[PDB]
Length: 58
Length: 50
Image 1 (cartoon, rainbow over the protein chains, first blue to last red):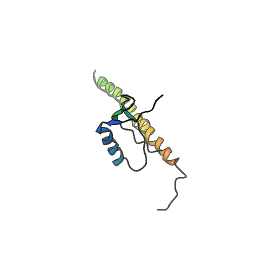
Image 2: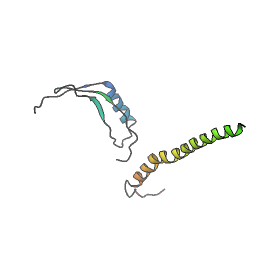
Image 3: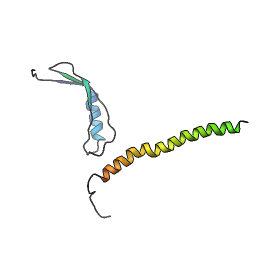
Image 4: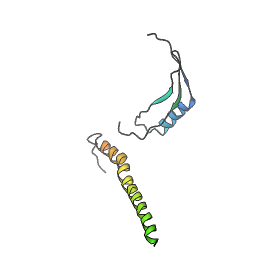
């Protein structure tokens, strides 16, 4: 019912798996799910970004 | 009377490795033929020349 400026305290492993997923992620665009914990209203954290199978269909 | 025991343990292993033959066929074919239908059903798949 109220809006505040949020923040994402990242685990670096998030961007590490994103860079592996993009480097090895051959330029066909791909999809996955992000895994953290909603700490509060003005911040969020991502502790994990897990991997997907080779969904080369769309 | 134990050659039949080794051969029947090998027949249980034959059923196991035949479930694995059907696994390497069908379970891998899930991935393979699913995404190969899906790559065949991408487009009228861009005809071309060798």
